[PDB]
Image (cartoon, rainbow, N blue to C red; front, side):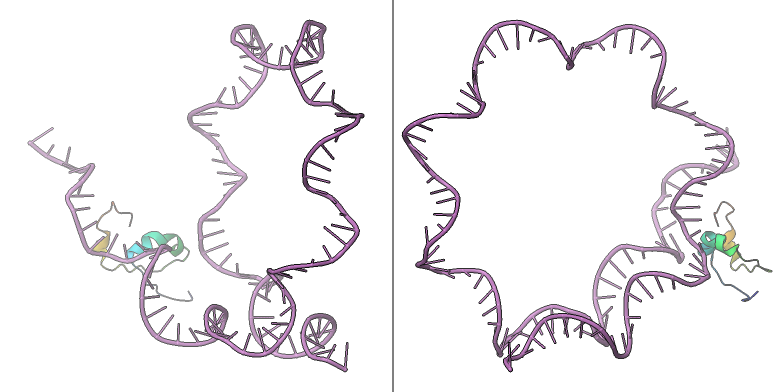
Length: 43
DNA sequence: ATATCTGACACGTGCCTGGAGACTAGGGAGTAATCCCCTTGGCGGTTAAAACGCGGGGGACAGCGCGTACGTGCGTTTAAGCGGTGCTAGAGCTGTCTACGACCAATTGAGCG
């Protein structure tokens, strides 16, 4: 891949997923993952 | 009775709208020089203005009759939902060419002879 690691936040990712899925990743890093505690969330 | 629901009620960040600050430099505001203008104002070939004598036809009937109105028949009109699924705008991105910038020639207006 031409550029390696991308830095993001949950408010962007829940809208931008359609763009991010245009590129594959080897590994996912998910920081303060308690942001995902609600399975009811759109996030 | 109980699981768990629908507010209460708030700060998360997104979006764009919307304001004010400090800069350049585009252009607006101040001015003469001077011209050339809107304007004032007498001139006589030409038509607004109104009678008299008069021509073209406006005016008020009688009633014939080629069309006009009602409003129900009856068979042809669009309604109407909701199946599939191609079109359609979003929208992400070029891949340039096309109209709009930067440097300087043919043709014009100004000067007066």
